[PDB]
Length: 388
Image (cartoon, rainbow, N blue to C red; front, side, top):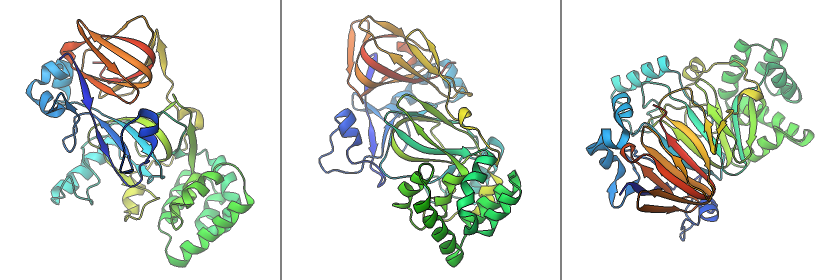
C-alpha cells in the first residue's frame, strides 16, 4: 500500500552479461539471455510495475500525491531513471551535448520529422541533464580527455601511426587534440589499417594501462579507430562504492563491470567510437570540449551524514544516496518520490503496520505522500529521489 515492491524490466541487449544479475541478485535467467540493464522507474517504453499496474500510469493519475508538489510543478513526471548496468562487452564512446546544442539538435530532428524511436534519432531532450554511475563490482570505463602531457607520453610509441598524431605532439594543445580526435575517427581504408597496425605493434612492446584496456576493447572492436581513445581519454577502474559523473561535451565509455546508473528519462547521445554505426564527425567535434580533465576531478566526492552517504548532483532532477542499514531503525524521508534499492545484505522497510523485505537487487517505490519510511537490517540501501 504505502511501499510498492517494484517489478522491474530487464533489457536484454546483446552486450549484456548472461550471469551478472543472477550471480549478484539471484534473478532468474534459464534461457541464458544477455541481461544488459535492469530498469527501475517509469519510462514510457518499459516502466516498472507495482502490485499489477504500470508505475507510470499510477503516477499519471495522482502526480502531486506520488511525485510531490515540487517535482510535479518542476517536471510533471518521474524525473529520473534508475538502472543496474551489466557491461559484459565494452560499449560505444558517447558524448552528451550541452543545453544550448541539445535544444538545436532536438529541434533540428523534430523539424525533419525524425521519430523518437528511430535509430537515426540522437537528440531526445531539449536539455542537458547529467548522469551518475556508481560501481557495484569493479567497473572499467573511460571518461574525459587526459592532461596534455599524459596524452603526449602515451602517443610517443604510436607517433608513426598517423600524421595528425605527430601534429599533436609538435604542439600539444586543444585545437590539435580536436584535429587528432576527428582525424582518428575519419580514418579510411589503408590509412586506418596503417594506424591500427602501428597500435597493435605497440601493444606487444608496451605494458600496463591504458594498453591493457586497449587489448580488452580490441577483442570486440578489432577494426575500430576508437582503439586509440584510451590514449586520449582517462581510463578509470572504479572500485565498488565509488561514483562518476558524465559531463557534457565529454567523451565517455563503459567498458566492463556492474554499476548503478541514474539519469534523466530522455538522453542525447553522439557516438564517438567503438561502434559500427555512422558518425557525423563535424557535429561531434562541434559538441566536444577538448579541455583536459585531471584524474582527481573524475570521481564524485560523496558526503556522509549519519548513516546516509549522499552523492551531490549539480541539478535538481535527481539525487543519489547510500544508506548503511543497521538493526536499529533509521528513518529515510524525502519531499519527493523515491526508489529504494537493496545493494547488499538485506533491508526491512516499515511504514506504520506495513513491512516490506528487500533482498539484494530488489527495489521499492515510495510515493511522496508515504514519506518517511523506517529502514533496518544489514548492508546498504541505495535511494534515488529529489532534494526539492
